[PDB]
Length: 132
RNA sequence: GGGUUCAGAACGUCGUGAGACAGUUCGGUCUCUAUCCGCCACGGGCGCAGGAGGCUUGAGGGGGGCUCUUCCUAGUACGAG
Image 1 (spheres, rainbow, N blue to C red):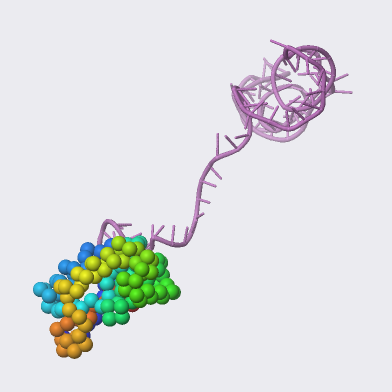
Image 2 (tube, rainbow, N blue to C red):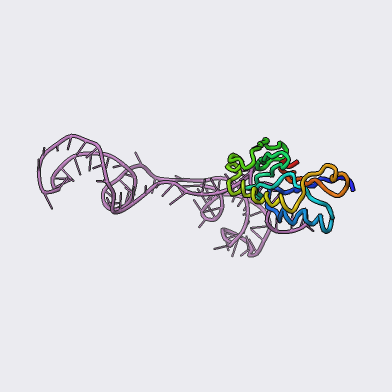
């Protein structure tokens, strides 16, 4: 029952779904999920994730793994610039979709993380360098 | 004018012989002047329902259209690999 952070590879293309996801580790596996960062578009239009304990959006770039694409952080949450660079609908879309995160999962607990029972959950794709 | 299709001449060859065999072999004169149609271009004559100097519309003609590699999407639809 030793710690074990979670990771979601393949953030370059589309995906089945962040909801029922971590949800099978509660029935079969048996471990609570604590999302520290969420999606911002799958596929080519992919736009990375966003940290929850840092309130700041990471912006990924197309094609890049050997030379990590420059890093760009748009802190300001619903702040327009984020919305504009990641698209309105989309930027507050996740906003409403992110709202879904407020309900159906927990926050981040350092002590339950090790005390065996939970797992920190990370999101990102290696082939991208974005999310490592 | 290399192949073949004139003389020489040579072998295999058939013919007694002269000779001969879409059998071989080496050798062997390709004719300065475009009149008429055509065609490439270039003028001179008259005409365009007044003399002129220009700049012009464009019916109708012509010209030209070709293709390869590699990178990005994207190691992603797809695929167990």
